[PDB]
Image (tube, rainbow over all chains, first blue to last red; front, side, top):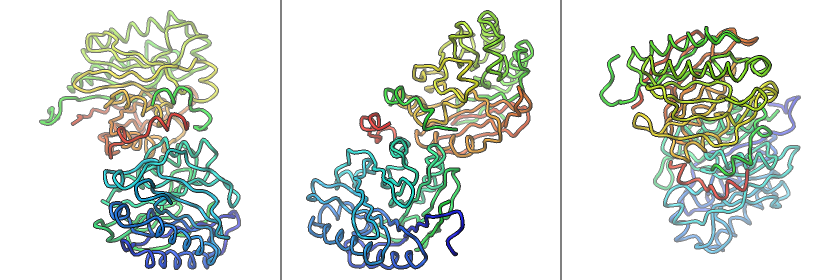
Length: 261
Length: 261
């Protein structure tokens, strides 16, 4: 609807099916979603993990060059500027195929990259064969009146990774993902706890449908700090648009915890 | 029922209402529950936080001596031996009123104390005025064919504390608690995630009913490693008896995590 009285941030999540190794098709889908999110008055669009090349880790490592990644990244900065909306995307990193990770970056509505992050927790042997894990903690930055942070897919299933973002001040954690296998426990059990246990909001934007030998679950969702969904999709392509409205972070005995992991 | 084919551990959880500052009444309730759990073929009974004196932190600090704590502890070791069941209880620690914490201990069916733990995460200003926080990680020990560990109440709401027990090999974490205020998010949202995110089972034994100026929620529950309740109570006194039947713990990048808390 109209932008509500108590809200000054409206975000959108893209859920769709990518075609493996067809960046012109996948980036056309992101441009469509960016235009539709901006028409509905959203200020930022979150898109799924590795969407521009499809979630095909082995084929990205074998077939996608650094120059082809940079061409998709330049197109995505162009979509943020041309559709006038901040955009979170996820691509392979910028180094050669043997030295890069899976990344997420946030561009503002002018197309400039505000923050970049490399996935720290790679999932399974295909990702670990195709990508280097990140070694830096999640970034946190002010945008739109709140402190935003980035994580990618499997990262959010580790409470440590969401605690690392909330310890640096995050209030809204944006998470491109690629979750297949009818893995109901991740959005149904873990995301609500990551929100409650830090008092944050998380946005989780998945693929859906048949892609890359998998059928992805959809179920994109935004979870607020009480653990309840502010909005959620089912299994088909869609664009979710949501208006955002114990002191664990202080109480935690972090100097003992860090010795006990 | 009869002990089932695929199970060699049957545990019980006591949920009841304690009378503040009346250890003879509260310990008589624990002895009743120990006898009833043992009759139903349970091998261990978990009881709630501070049950022997009631959950009355300020009054425990002002009025309960070390000698009165030791008298209750000796009675509880006597109930484990005399009712022939392992028992997890929670009392103030053994030091003077100004130097002790809130503890949990496990005695075997011979009455001997196998493990002791002091609550690391104290909840609120009343507990922090009445007790010293613990400084050691949760213990883990073999009993009954599995690795058991102890945490107390607020501790389990910190993913770090449950991760510290599962990192030392815990499979079954036993948690005396005292949760009031219709705090549905703890058993409904956080406990299932603590089970899934470590692949463990957790048992959470609450007070219920009017005690100490609070009305406790009940809702005692055992959660298995898929996050689903193996058994659960409502708001009234009861004895829950349950038969017990991604590689996060390996995948976590603990050397990075410990720098980022």
